Structures are given as C-alpha cells and as structure tokens.
Length: 125
Image (cartoon, rainbow, N blue to C red):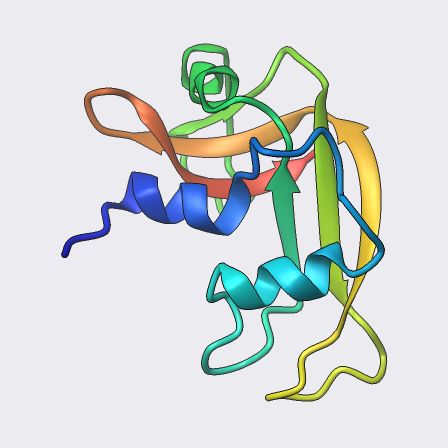
C-alpha cells in the first residue's frame, strides 16, 4: 500500500460525511480513528466538514504566505464548517483527550501535484 501526501491530508483533516462535529466526543473519536495519536498526543488538529471537491478548489484561490514563509499556500474564498480539536488539561499520552469546538472560517492550505491539491493544513482564519 502507498499513502500520498494528498491522501494524508484527507486522513488528517477532511470529514465530508458530517455537516459539523457529530457529538461532544467527536474529537476524541476522530483523533484516534484517523491515527493522529500513535506516538504522542497531537495538541491541535482541524477537521473540515466540506466536500472534497470544494476543499481541493482552494488550491486555485487566494495565494498567500504559509506561516513558515513558504509561498505554496492558498486561502479559501469561502467560509467553511470546521471542528478544532484541542488537548484537554488532563490529556496524557497514551490516553489522549480532546475538547471539540465548532467554527465557520476561511482555511489556509499548502498545495502540490497534478492534480494540484492540498497536502498541508496551515491555519483557519
């Protein structure tokens, strides 16, 4: 089996199957099932509740600097439904624990390839 960087972005950041976080346990559930918490707790992670076609479209939208200075980042015109997963104060590997928060924000992603698609989640703004 092979996993491309594009496929890794889908696993770590896409959930097209729901319009928003489905429960208060959503982040606990997803951080585990998407294998984000293997070797250490990932302290923050964003999931985007939008079609894959709509998120892939961002790579032809507003070119902006990534927060590390690189210039293959793009900001969405549209406002997207997202969930922010943030570690709780009591979270301690291997028993990682997250609070689920909901928002509606533009996203910034880094893009590569043909088709030109997201491979990195930079920020929501």
